[PDB]
Amino acid sequence: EDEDVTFNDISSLSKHVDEGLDGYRDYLIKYSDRELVQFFENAQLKRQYGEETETVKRDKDEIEKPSIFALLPAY
Amino acid sequence: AELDSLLGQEKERFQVLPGRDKMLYVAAQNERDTLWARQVLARGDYDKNARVINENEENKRISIWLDTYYPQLAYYRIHFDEPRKPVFWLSRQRNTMSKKELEVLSQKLRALMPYADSVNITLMDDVTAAGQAEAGLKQQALPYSRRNHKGGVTFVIQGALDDVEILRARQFVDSYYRTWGGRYVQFAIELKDDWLKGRSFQYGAEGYIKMSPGHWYFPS
Amino acid sequence: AELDSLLGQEKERFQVLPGRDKMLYVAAQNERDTLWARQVLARGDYDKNARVINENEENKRISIWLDTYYPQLAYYRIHFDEPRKPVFWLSRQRNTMSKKELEVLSQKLRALMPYADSVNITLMDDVTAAGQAEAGLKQQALPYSRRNHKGGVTFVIQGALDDVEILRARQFVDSYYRTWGGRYVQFAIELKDDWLKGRSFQYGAEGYIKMSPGHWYFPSPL
Amino acid sequence: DKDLLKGLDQEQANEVIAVLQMHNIEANKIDSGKLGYSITVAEPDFTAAVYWIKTYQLPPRPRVEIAQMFPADSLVSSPRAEKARLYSAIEQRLEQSLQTMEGVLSARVHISYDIDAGENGRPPKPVHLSALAVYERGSPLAHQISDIKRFLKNSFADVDYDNISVVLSERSDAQLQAPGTPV
Amino acid sequence: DKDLLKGLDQEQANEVIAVLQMHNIEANKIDSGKLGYSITVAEPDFTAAVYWIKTYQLPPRPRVEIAQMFPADSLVSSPRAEKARLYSAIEQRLEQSLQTMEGVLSARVHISYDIDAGENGRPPKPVHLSALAVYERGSPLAHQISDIKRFLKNSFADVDYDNISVVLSERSDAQLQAPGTPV
Amino acid sequence: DKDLLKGLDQEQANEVIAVLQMHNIEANKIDSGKLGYSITVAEPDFTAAVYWIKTYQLPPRPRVEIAQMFPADSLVSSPRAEKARLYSAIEQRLEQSLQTMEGVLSARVHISYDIDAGENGRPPKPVHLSALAVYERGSPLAHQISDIKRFLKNSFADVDYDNISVVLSERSDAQLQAPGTPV
Amino acid sequence: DKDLLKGLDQEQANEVIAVLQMHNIEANKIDSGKLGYSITVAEPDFTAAVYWIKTYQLPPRPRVEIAQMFPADSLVSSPRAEKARLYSAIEQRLEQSLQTMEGVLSARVHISYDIDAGENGRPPKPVHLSALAVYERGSPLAHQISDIKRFLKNSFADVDYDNISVVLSERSDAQLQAPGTPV
């Protein structure tokens, strides 16, 4: 409920809505295991993948942004 | 049993002088040695009169006497490298005295020191003193500020000094003070916290510090 | 029982000189040897008067006396390679004295050193000293800054130094100090969390420009 | 002769004798076995010896190490105790290493204990270190601080030269000549 | 002779003797073994000795240390008690380290016990320190405070020079000559 | 002769004798079997011997190793203890390996025990290493630091030349001539 | 004759004798059976023998192997212990194999112990190896490093030539002539 925002595209809106949930995301990250979270984060994708390398994204984004469906059962 | 035979094997560690008051004066170089000597007398091993003396104690006693009879005399320190003929350094600018007055002063000092045959008065330059202080601070590459007052100079050394700096400064200050004393030039060492580490800031005429995004601090 | 017979089997380690004050002076090379000798005397194995001396102690003592009677004399060091004829190095540019004054100075030094027959005074060049200092730094390829003052030169070596650099630096400095002393040229070695090793630059529309020297340094984010 | 102290340990007796000798007081050490050591002095020196024993608070208390407070013989231990023992053993092993450097006579080292944190869901603070050391006479202290800092920096996962304090001092003059006997 | 005190410990007796000698009172120490030491004085000095024993509140109490309130021989330790023992051992180790600095004769250190709360739920507060020390005569106290502050700053995770208090004092005059015996 | 110390171990005794001989003090070692070794000196040398024993804090402490805080005799083990024992055994095996290099007389090595965090959840940190060594006279120290660094780098999963500190020193002058006997 | 050391074992005794003979000190080994071996020297050589015993830190304490911390003979074992024993056996078997190559007199090998993490869930990390070896005089060391690297590379599932460090040295001059007996 914040009347000063403005958007231009589906991406710019997605980002702002995701940013809204970080308050909850942080709580789940605090109380759950990093490695089980990472395992499910792999399992959502890697049935797609032709490759073994995981470094391909440097951690600083993905460590902050595990998905909520990955966080829930791990919590 | 002479006194020299009672002070130890290291004969030259101590120096015995006769005083006109019929008393022996033992000259020592430091506190530890002073107490090594004083124990012998306080035990009462020797039957005649004797006394133990050192340069810092004598400087203090003489300054206390000057405080009473010459409360406006400007001077530095008295050197006792040759205990029979001390050297007294006076300021050339901050005093005016005639030769007669200087002689009278000389004789009264000689009366205070019954072990000295004469006192040599030498006039020293304040500009020289101040210059040797500043040159030494520069040679040591310490950061400093200089303040001038009518009767003295003050060097302030303040900030987040390092261990190597603290050590160098301490050594230097202690070297200077043993030559010139602490009357004309004073040094002040002041450790304080660092505000800039990890903060963005603007410096120059209009400086300010970013405490955090959205918070500006303006210093005086 | 002469003193030489009491100091040991390694006769060559020590040198015994007769002093004009009726006292034996034992010349040593280092602290460990100095204490090896002093134990003999302090135990009281020898009955006559004797004293132990070394070059660093004597340099200190003589400088303390100069501080009182010649408070403005500019000088480097007194060498005792041949203890009967020491060599005293004076600056040429910073002193100004006549031959008579030099002779008087010579005689007063001789009066302070009852084991020396004469003192030879030699004039040395400051530019030479400073040049040898900088040449040795470049020869080691140490990173450094030079600062000049009326009375002296200061070389600063600071930042994230490496083990090999630290070793070379300490060795060089310790070699130089033994020749020229620490009166004219100073070396300051300080470790800082600074990858540039004291260089500093500011960025602007034309590119980088070098900063001036200063106390402030930017800790390396890397 | 008057009795100053009784029932001393070996190291205590030797420290007391050293301090009395420094001030020109001739003292005697006697061994009674199960009863320990006794120290005695002459009457002319009794007063002074009392004043120095007061001023230095002799005999010395025993040396304190943090592992003493969490005896390992316990049937139960928290993580806090284990972590404490660990740090208190690293401090000792570093002082034992520093004493082997060239010219060092002794050293003492302190580490920032942060084991008082539970570290629950919480980032670890950086480590801080302090050291004292004594050198042989004629050592360039200024040039020797660098070596110590360099050596300490890499002994821990995260230490900055800014966070290391080092204080150095030289050995005092040697006490070689014996004190004089009262007449 | 009149009896002043009985059943003293050795370190209590020497403190009493030292304080009486300073005021020119000749005292005698006697040993009864399992019964301890006894102190006696002459009648002309009895009055003065009584008044000084009152004024200084001799004999001295035993030394207090916080670890005595939370002895490790207990079946359960709270997170409060363990943390307290820890701090109470660090205090003593710092005092013993400062006593090794050049010129220092004795010292004391105090640390802020935040453990008087668990620090449950709330985050921890910053640490505060205080120290006292005695120096040998002729020491530049002003220039020596810096070293102490520098050394203490790095022994803890978060300390500011503003939060460190240091108080220094010099040794009093030496009591070397013996008191005169009553006529 | 005056007694300096009693009940020494063999390795304590030989270190004391070495330190006295270096300062020209002739000492004697006596064996009492179950009572250990005793050290004695002449009166003219007693004072000096006392001063040196104080200055060097003799007799030496026994050598610490971290495995001593977590005995394998423990009734139970946590992961922290096992990991500690592991690291404390690797340090010793590396020192024993370095002594086999050409010219090295002795060395000491230290490791980052990051185990103090049991790595519950948190990822591991990289290792840091420190080493000291003593060389035979006439060794090009500058050229020999490289070999040590090269050797240590590959002993661990992740180490950078930047994270390895090495300090080297030469052997002191040899003590070959015997001390003089008091007259 | 003066006693240097008592209660030695066979390997410590032969090590001391070797070191003393190298410096021209004639020594004697005596066997007391259940009491072990004793080493003795003449008085003129006592001082030197003491100085070398200190400088080399003799006698040598015995060789450390990582399996000694997690002794296989136990009622219980855990994955960390099993994995540790495994690696500590491969290390020893490789050193024993290298000593069979042509010219090698002795060698030592080290492996990166990744077991200090469980490697459960966390992905396992690649191996690093280090080797030291001593050769007979007149060996082309440069040409022989290649063979060692080639041999070591294939002993593990994933090793890169970049991750293998090898340091080689030659045997010192032979000590064949006997030392001279004091006159």
Image: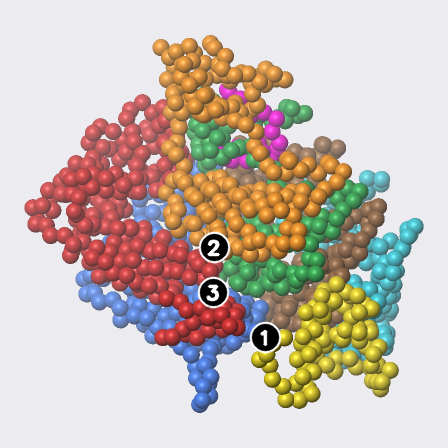
Chain colours: A yellow, B red, C blue, D green, E orange, F brown, G cyan
Q: Do we see residue G180 in this rendering?
A: no
Q: Quadrant of residue B70?
A: top left
Determine if the magenta segment contains residue C196: no
Type of amino acid at the residue the image marks with label 3: Trp
Type of amino acid at the residue the image marks with label 1: Leu
Q: Residue at x 28, y 33 (%)?
A: B25
CA separation in Å, label 1 and label 2 = 29 Å
Q: Which residue is mark 3?
A: B195
Instruction: Kindly state the secondary structure of the residue where label 1 is placed.
Output: loop
Instruction: Give the left or right position of residue G14, taking residue D55 as reference.
Output: right
Chain under disc 1: C
The answer as to whether the residues below labels 1 and 2 share one chain is no
CA separation in Å, label 3 and label 2 = 13 Å
Which label sits in the foreground, 1 or 2?
2
Q: Quadrant of the C terminus of chain E?
A: top left
Type of amino acid at the residue the image marks with label 2: Tyr
Q: Which residues are magenta?
A: D1-21
Q: Residue at x 48, y 30 (%)?
A: D54
Q: Identify the disc placed on residue E161.
A: 2
Q: Residues within 10 Å of mark 3 (few under 14, many from 20)?
A: few
Instruction: Kindly state the secondary structure of the residue where label 3 is placed.
Output: loop
Chain under disc 2: E
